[PDB]
Length: 364
Ligand SMILES: CC(C)[C@H](N)C(=O)O
Ligand SMILES: [Mg+2]
Image (cartoon, rainbow, N blue to C red; front, side, top):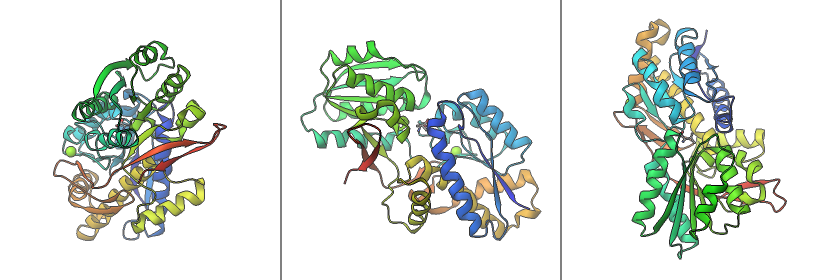
């Protein structure tokens, strides 16, 4: 006997350039927690249902997990775009959802069954603008790009634009693109003609990487910030040496000294031969929230005897009250499921000259 927890992430499509790191973190969590006896001796069982890259696929994944797989709760989905469509399904069904990486404004507000462990754009994004200004205090002109079809990108770009204004900088253009575009020559040229000192990009990974590469190809030599959708080593293949120097805010640091981060990091590095990325740590934290909440609930009200609808409702109630020492740091939730988290960072892509290898360097 095991306790089923649903994992609904993008395992296919270009959205999997983000989702695959989340899957990796979830699997590390499953082993970590099951090796510790699961829920008071009862193992958990992660049930993975691929969402693919759109809303329909996410809705289908959620419905399958809820109805066929009888899960006690869901971790997912990957994108805020998917969450706004699918999370109401879980809300209506009274099944908890813990978002690992949905950072758009409004996610926890979807309902009483929706929480997230991922700090939102309003607190994450401004960090990278400040870091760019530290590296070049003479930045004056800023060009902004965003994916107009993606909910998170639209939410993130508003924060970047407001931050640019509040820092007293000149916003010289806002250019739009689609996440499915591969070519950005006209937008990139129109921005470059305005002589920006800083370029900020809110898109996802393939699109963001292609845009970075093209800006450099077209002669742009200024600073570049990527938003959360570029926050993956999967961009390295796309922009190669021309990824070098891109600044990306972080809601996780491998060097954070919390005991569980040490264990998570060691497990990750031993397997993948590089530092754990933010998305992996966030997925681990989401699974941790479920395991620790299930343990607390089970101690007070043995879960093997609770029928599923009540188990789901009691688990949701429990998780919202918990405090968790996770790889992300000490976190908890507001009464509506927003994460409470203290520390943020900025990292910078450092490519090797040949362009075939790189890493994220954390700024001090
Ligand atoms: C990069 C992506 C996972 C983004 N944080 C979102 O909310 O969709
Ligand atoms: Mg909520």
